[PDB]
């Protein structure tokens, strides 16, 4: 996944 | 206290689980797994957020696990470090  | 959750209401695993009522049908991870790792649904895409550190995770890939993504990207989260 991609973190923000 | 010396730590403070970004979202106190989502302190509860049950509250986090409820947030997935409208989790999209394409999103492969289960609400059970996500909520157990501290994560609740933001209502946008497949984007979840941690009640503790406030980190957000989206664009989940096959083979991703909730806990391992949470720890990889937000290793200093108190929920990660308290587990
Ligand atoms: Zn966190």
Image: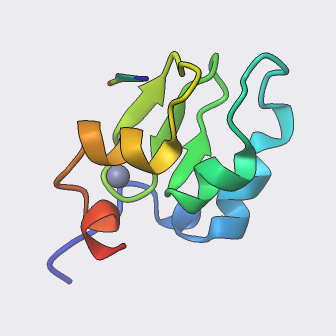
Q: Position of residue B68 (x, y in %)?
A: 39, 45
Q: Report whether B7 appears left or right of B55.
A: right
**Image: B29 above or below B79:** above
- The residue depicted at 72 percent of the width and 46 percent of the height is B31
Q: Position of residue B4 (x, y in %)?
A: 28, 68
**Image: B26 above or below B48:** above
**Image: B2 above or below B6:** below
**Image: A3 above or below B34:** above
Label count reads 0
Looking at this rendering, what residue extends furthest in the bottom direction? B1
Q: Position of residue B1 (x, y in %)?
A: 20, 83
Looking at this rendering, what residue extends furthest in the front direction? B63
Find residue B22 and report its image quarter: top right
**Colour treatment of the image:** rainbow
- The residue depicted at 54 percent of the width and 22 percent of the height is B60
Q: Report whether B72 appears left or right of B52.
A: left
- The residue depicted at 55 percent of the width and 26 percent of the height is B47
Along the line of sight, the residue nearer the viewer: B43 or B83: B83
Find residue B55 and report its image quarter: top left
Q: Report whether B44 appears left or right of B70.
A: right
Q: Position of residue B38 (x, y in %)?
A: 50, 57
Along the line of sight, the residue nearer the viewer: B64 or B18: B64
Along the line of sight, the residue nearer the viewer: B32 or B68: B68
Can you say which quadrant of the picture contains the C terminus of chain B?
bottom left
Along the line of sight, the residue nearer the viewer: B42 or B59: B59
């Amino acid at each position: 996944a991609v973190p923000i | 206290g010396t730590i403070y959750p970004r979202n106190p209401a989502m302190y509860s695993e049950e509250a986090r689980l409820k947030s997935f009522q409208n989790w999209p049908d394409y999103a492969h991870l289960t609400p059970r797994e996500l909520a157990s790792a501290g994560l609740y649904y933001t209502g946008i895409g497949d984007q979840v957020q941690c009640f503790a550190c406030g980190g957000k995770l989206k664009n989940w890939e096959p083979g991703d696990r909730a806990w391992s993504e949470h720890r990889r990207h937000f290793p200093n989260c108190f929920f990660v470090l308290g587990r």
